Image (tube, coloured by chain):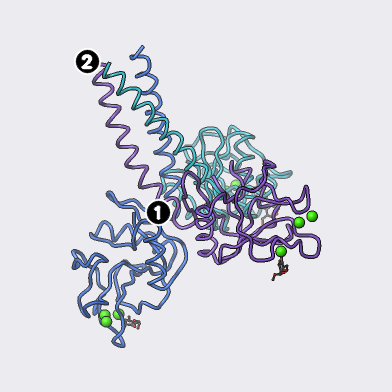
Chain colours: A cyan, B purple, C blue
Amino acid sequence: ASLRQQVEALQGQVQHLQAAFSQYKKVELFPNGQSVGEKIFKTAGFVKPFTEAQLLCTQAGGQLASPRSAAENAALQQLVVAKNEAAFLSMTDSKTEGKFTYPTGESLVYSNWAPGEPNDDGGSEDCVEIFTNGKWNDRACGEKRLVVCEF
Amino acid sequence: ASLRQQVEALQGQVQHLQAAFSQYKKVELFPNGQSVGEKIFKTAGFVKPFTEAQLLCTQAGGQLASPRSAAENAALQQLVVAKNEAAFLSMTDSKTEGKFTYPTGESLVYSNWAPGEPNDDGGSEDCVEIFTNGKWNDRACGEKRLVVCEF
Amino acid sequence: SLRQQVEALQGQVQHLQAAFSQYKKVELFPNGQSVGEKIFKTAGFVKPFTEAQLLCTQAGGQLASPRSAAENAALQQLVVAKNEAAFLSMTDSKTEGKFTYPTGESLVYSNWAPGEPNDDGGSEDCVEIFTNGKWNDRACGEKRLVVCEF
Ligand SMILES: CO[C@H]1O[C@H](CO)[C@@H](O)[C@H](O)[C@@H]1O
Ligand SMILES: CO[C@H]1O[C@H](CO)[C@@H](O)[C@H](O)[C@@H]1O
Ligand SMILES: CO[C@H]1O[C@H](CO)[C@@H](O)[C@H](O)[C@@H]1O
Ligand SMILES: [Ca+2]
Ligand SMILES: [Ca+2]
Ligand SMILES: [Ca+2]
Ligand SMILES: [Ca+2]
Ligand SMILES: [Ca+2]
Ligand SMILES: [Ca+2]
Ligand SMILES: [Ca+2]
Ligand SMILES: [Ca+2]
Ligand SMILES: [Ca+2]
């Protein structure tokens, strides 16, 4: 019976914590983040070449944005539109030209290539950017694009 | 007893979350947030016209800053001062000239109008801005002001 | 019954632990660094010392006060990322040649650049940290990156 008092008390504490956490999470995502499902995109708000962007996300405990569905892509698109800057995705075909993979080596399960893409322009486009319209284009890894990580 | 031991373990886990979260609350609100009572204001740090500002807030699960007491208004003022940029509030008299309402249609429970305001200058001021001195002025919705949401 | 409520509570706490851990990463990116029990966060802009100090105290923290090589290296990452030297909390405003924390305590760790502190011009009572992590005394009226600790 004293255990029941403790349980009822802990239940109230945990629910107040859930409520505070939920509020702080909305605050956290405004205006540089987007949640979609269990994934959270957050932009750093500046641009970097791919290798540097990739390092920022991994050091932060995440990875570069990797939309795996239309819904994820739409969420990511909101951030790009808000910053009005194309962003890098995580995926590259550096290992095998024409074959884009996630950092793990897995093949794409979703893509949203703009018409005519990916075209490996100049013979050297192995990174991927997402435009303000949400479509993707292969782009040289040395160009600077908005940094958006996923967690 | 096992139920007892489970409750004790939960107690320890909850204490740890409360303590860890309490620190992150402070970190999160620096430098663009302000907590007051159960409300949190958060600025995007940039300016937009009203309609755009309102959409940003509502899409983020909030609404434009709606100070409902002197205490809230002072907390909001601290952000406005820090950014040195007047901000939009949520309230308008777009529906009925002279009758300012919250986005829910409720009439105002607090106001801090500068002397002689609102004055519907030019016959077309239906939004409200808050100055760095904390006072309110009705202003054209088309103008660009600091975006500050409440959560 | 009780055993059921406990089970549900267990689920709620495990969910919060996972959600909180994910949220911590989101929060610290890109302007924060966690080191031990301390968190540094930069505002991403520069201010003169008095203004920087007030921003930190009103936010419920204080200016970055690295107390070990580990803390200094963590702080240094933010400085390197913004490519902007930052103010520390410590000053010798009260007693020239003696730098103290905002409490009044004397320094328990330092990382002065060679020759520093040198009170150049007879008026350097604040401290900046460079992208190389070394410290230099500097006029309090100059504008440097604001970084607070919590
Ligand atoms: C859309 O812009 C064009 O040029 C860029 C690189 O500059 C390409 O990546 C792209 O596929 C097009 O050919
Ligand atoms: C300086 O402020 C004046 O003009 C603006 C519009 O420019 C008004 O909203 C205000 O009430 C005053 O008439
Ligand atoms: C370039 O560095 C020198 O000048 C600055 C600015 O005055 C001093 O703080 C420093 O100790 C050196 O004398
Ligand atoms: Ca190639
Ligand atoms: Ca290629
Ligand atoms: Ca291309
Ligand atoms: Ca009108
Ligand atoms: Ca009006
Ligand atoms: Ca007016
Ligand atoms: Ca002195
Ligand atoms: Ca000095
Ligand atoms: Ca010096």
**Is residue C116 positioned above or below B15 on the image?**
below
Q: What residue is shown at x 69% (from left), y 47% (from top)?
A: B101
| Quadrant in the rendering for residue B111 | bottom right
Please state the chain letter of the residue tagged with numbered disc 1 in the rendered image. Answer: C
- Amino acid at dot 2: Ala
Foreground: A78 or C52? C52
Foreground: C92 or C24? C92
Q: Residue furthest bottom?
A: C121
Quarter in which the N terminus of chain C is drawn: top left
**Looking at the picture, how far across and down is residue A134, in whole percent?**
67, 44
* Tag in front: 2 or 1: 2
**Is residue B39 positioned above or below C116 on the image?**
above
The residue singled out by tag 1 in the image is: C32
The residue singled out by tag 2 in the image is: B1
Quarter in which the C terminus of chain C is drawn: bottom left
**Is residue C5 positioned above or below C37 on the image?**
above
Residues tagged by mark 2 and mark 1 found on one chain of the structure = no
**Looking at the picture, how far across and down is residue B14, in whole percent?**
32, 33
- Amino acid at dot 1: Gly
Q: Measure how far apart labels 2 and 1 are at the Cα level.
A: 43 Å
Q: Secondary structure at mark 1?
A: strand
Foreground: A42 or B118? B118
Q: Give the number of the disc on residue C83.
A: none
Q: Secondary structure at mark 2?
A: loop
Cβ–Cβ below 8 Å for labels 2 and 1? no
Q: Is residue C115 left or right of residue A52?
A: left
Q: Residues within 10 Å of mark 2 (few under 14, many from 20)?
A: few
Label 2 near ligand 5 (CB < 8 Å): no
| Quadrant in the rendering for residue C147 | bottom left
